[PDB]
Image (cartoon, rainbow over all chains, first blue to last red; front, side, top):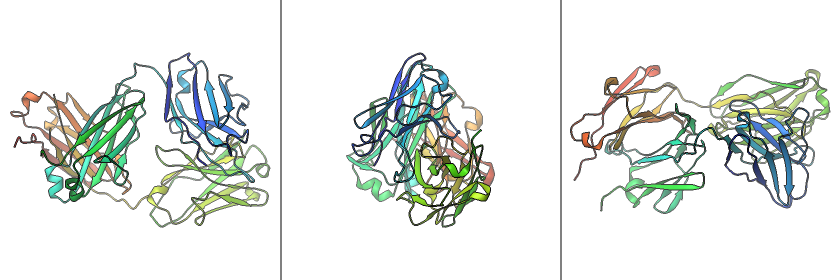
Length: 215
Length: 211
């Protein structure tokens, strides 16, 4: 069974933050086997907490773990810049126990004011459609923290097929940029009243919409 | 110190197989399980299975049953993971980790599954302060450089990092924010360069004609 983590959490230096990991009564609710891993960009994960609350030798006492019901939680006190990383919860794997990891949580240690994304949605060009192809282009920039959720809709219905989204990458100003592309056939583009790019940042969702015709 | 060393990065075509090794040092190999986990680029950790280094007994994740094999050679303290009938979405860093708690991880083995070969982009105008741009589709490998008006236009230009598509090809967009008053009088041309394929494209971006 899946373990659910928030997509992203953030805090300022010196502050305390908590990352949740929700399972079911059959997994997290039954065993003291939830572990937490820290992963820096381009590095292998590192075990921070095992067995819900135990720290391996050498791990800072600023990291602690707990559990209540079906939710295990990692708490980091006195946030330092080096704490900025992705964090995963997972269960013990071996013997009768099958492994599972949570989806991960990006932790940002705030170094500048939070900034909402600037979103621009472009419809397929006349040239691309003439070439019997169609691509919707959703450009997301100047956001901080560097975590977003991008989703697409065909009219009011969700669409997953033909979607290619980048992971956020740091711009020269330390804010982030990301982009998402939706590939369609020219018929799919003209058959719908509209297509939408939905961008969620820090619990704020903006939806940009394009239509194939003016009336 | 406990260490798990993994074999080197590989690139495989769809349908092929890959065999990753994981060699232990700094502890007694047979005293702990070896777990296998993978991570697609920008995605999360995914468990693949566990092997008991004493018996060689295995547990495979349901998602991979039928095409994943795990073995070990205790004489050289090495565990192996072989994944067959590779797909594009098997592109990932593959890790081994020690014990049920995954308390030490190997450095990871990057496996890319692709049939992509050198290809120049197709460029499309993104008609329009106003935002206008150029869509640079389906090229391989990186990089593409984009200039505007042969380098005359630099202010307000943002060329986005490329998306690496499930097809194995890249696409990117370059956008420029300009005063909306200039749309009727100023010409905007993006100049796309893809040195690996020796392709250069100049594309005029016209304002989205009223009526």
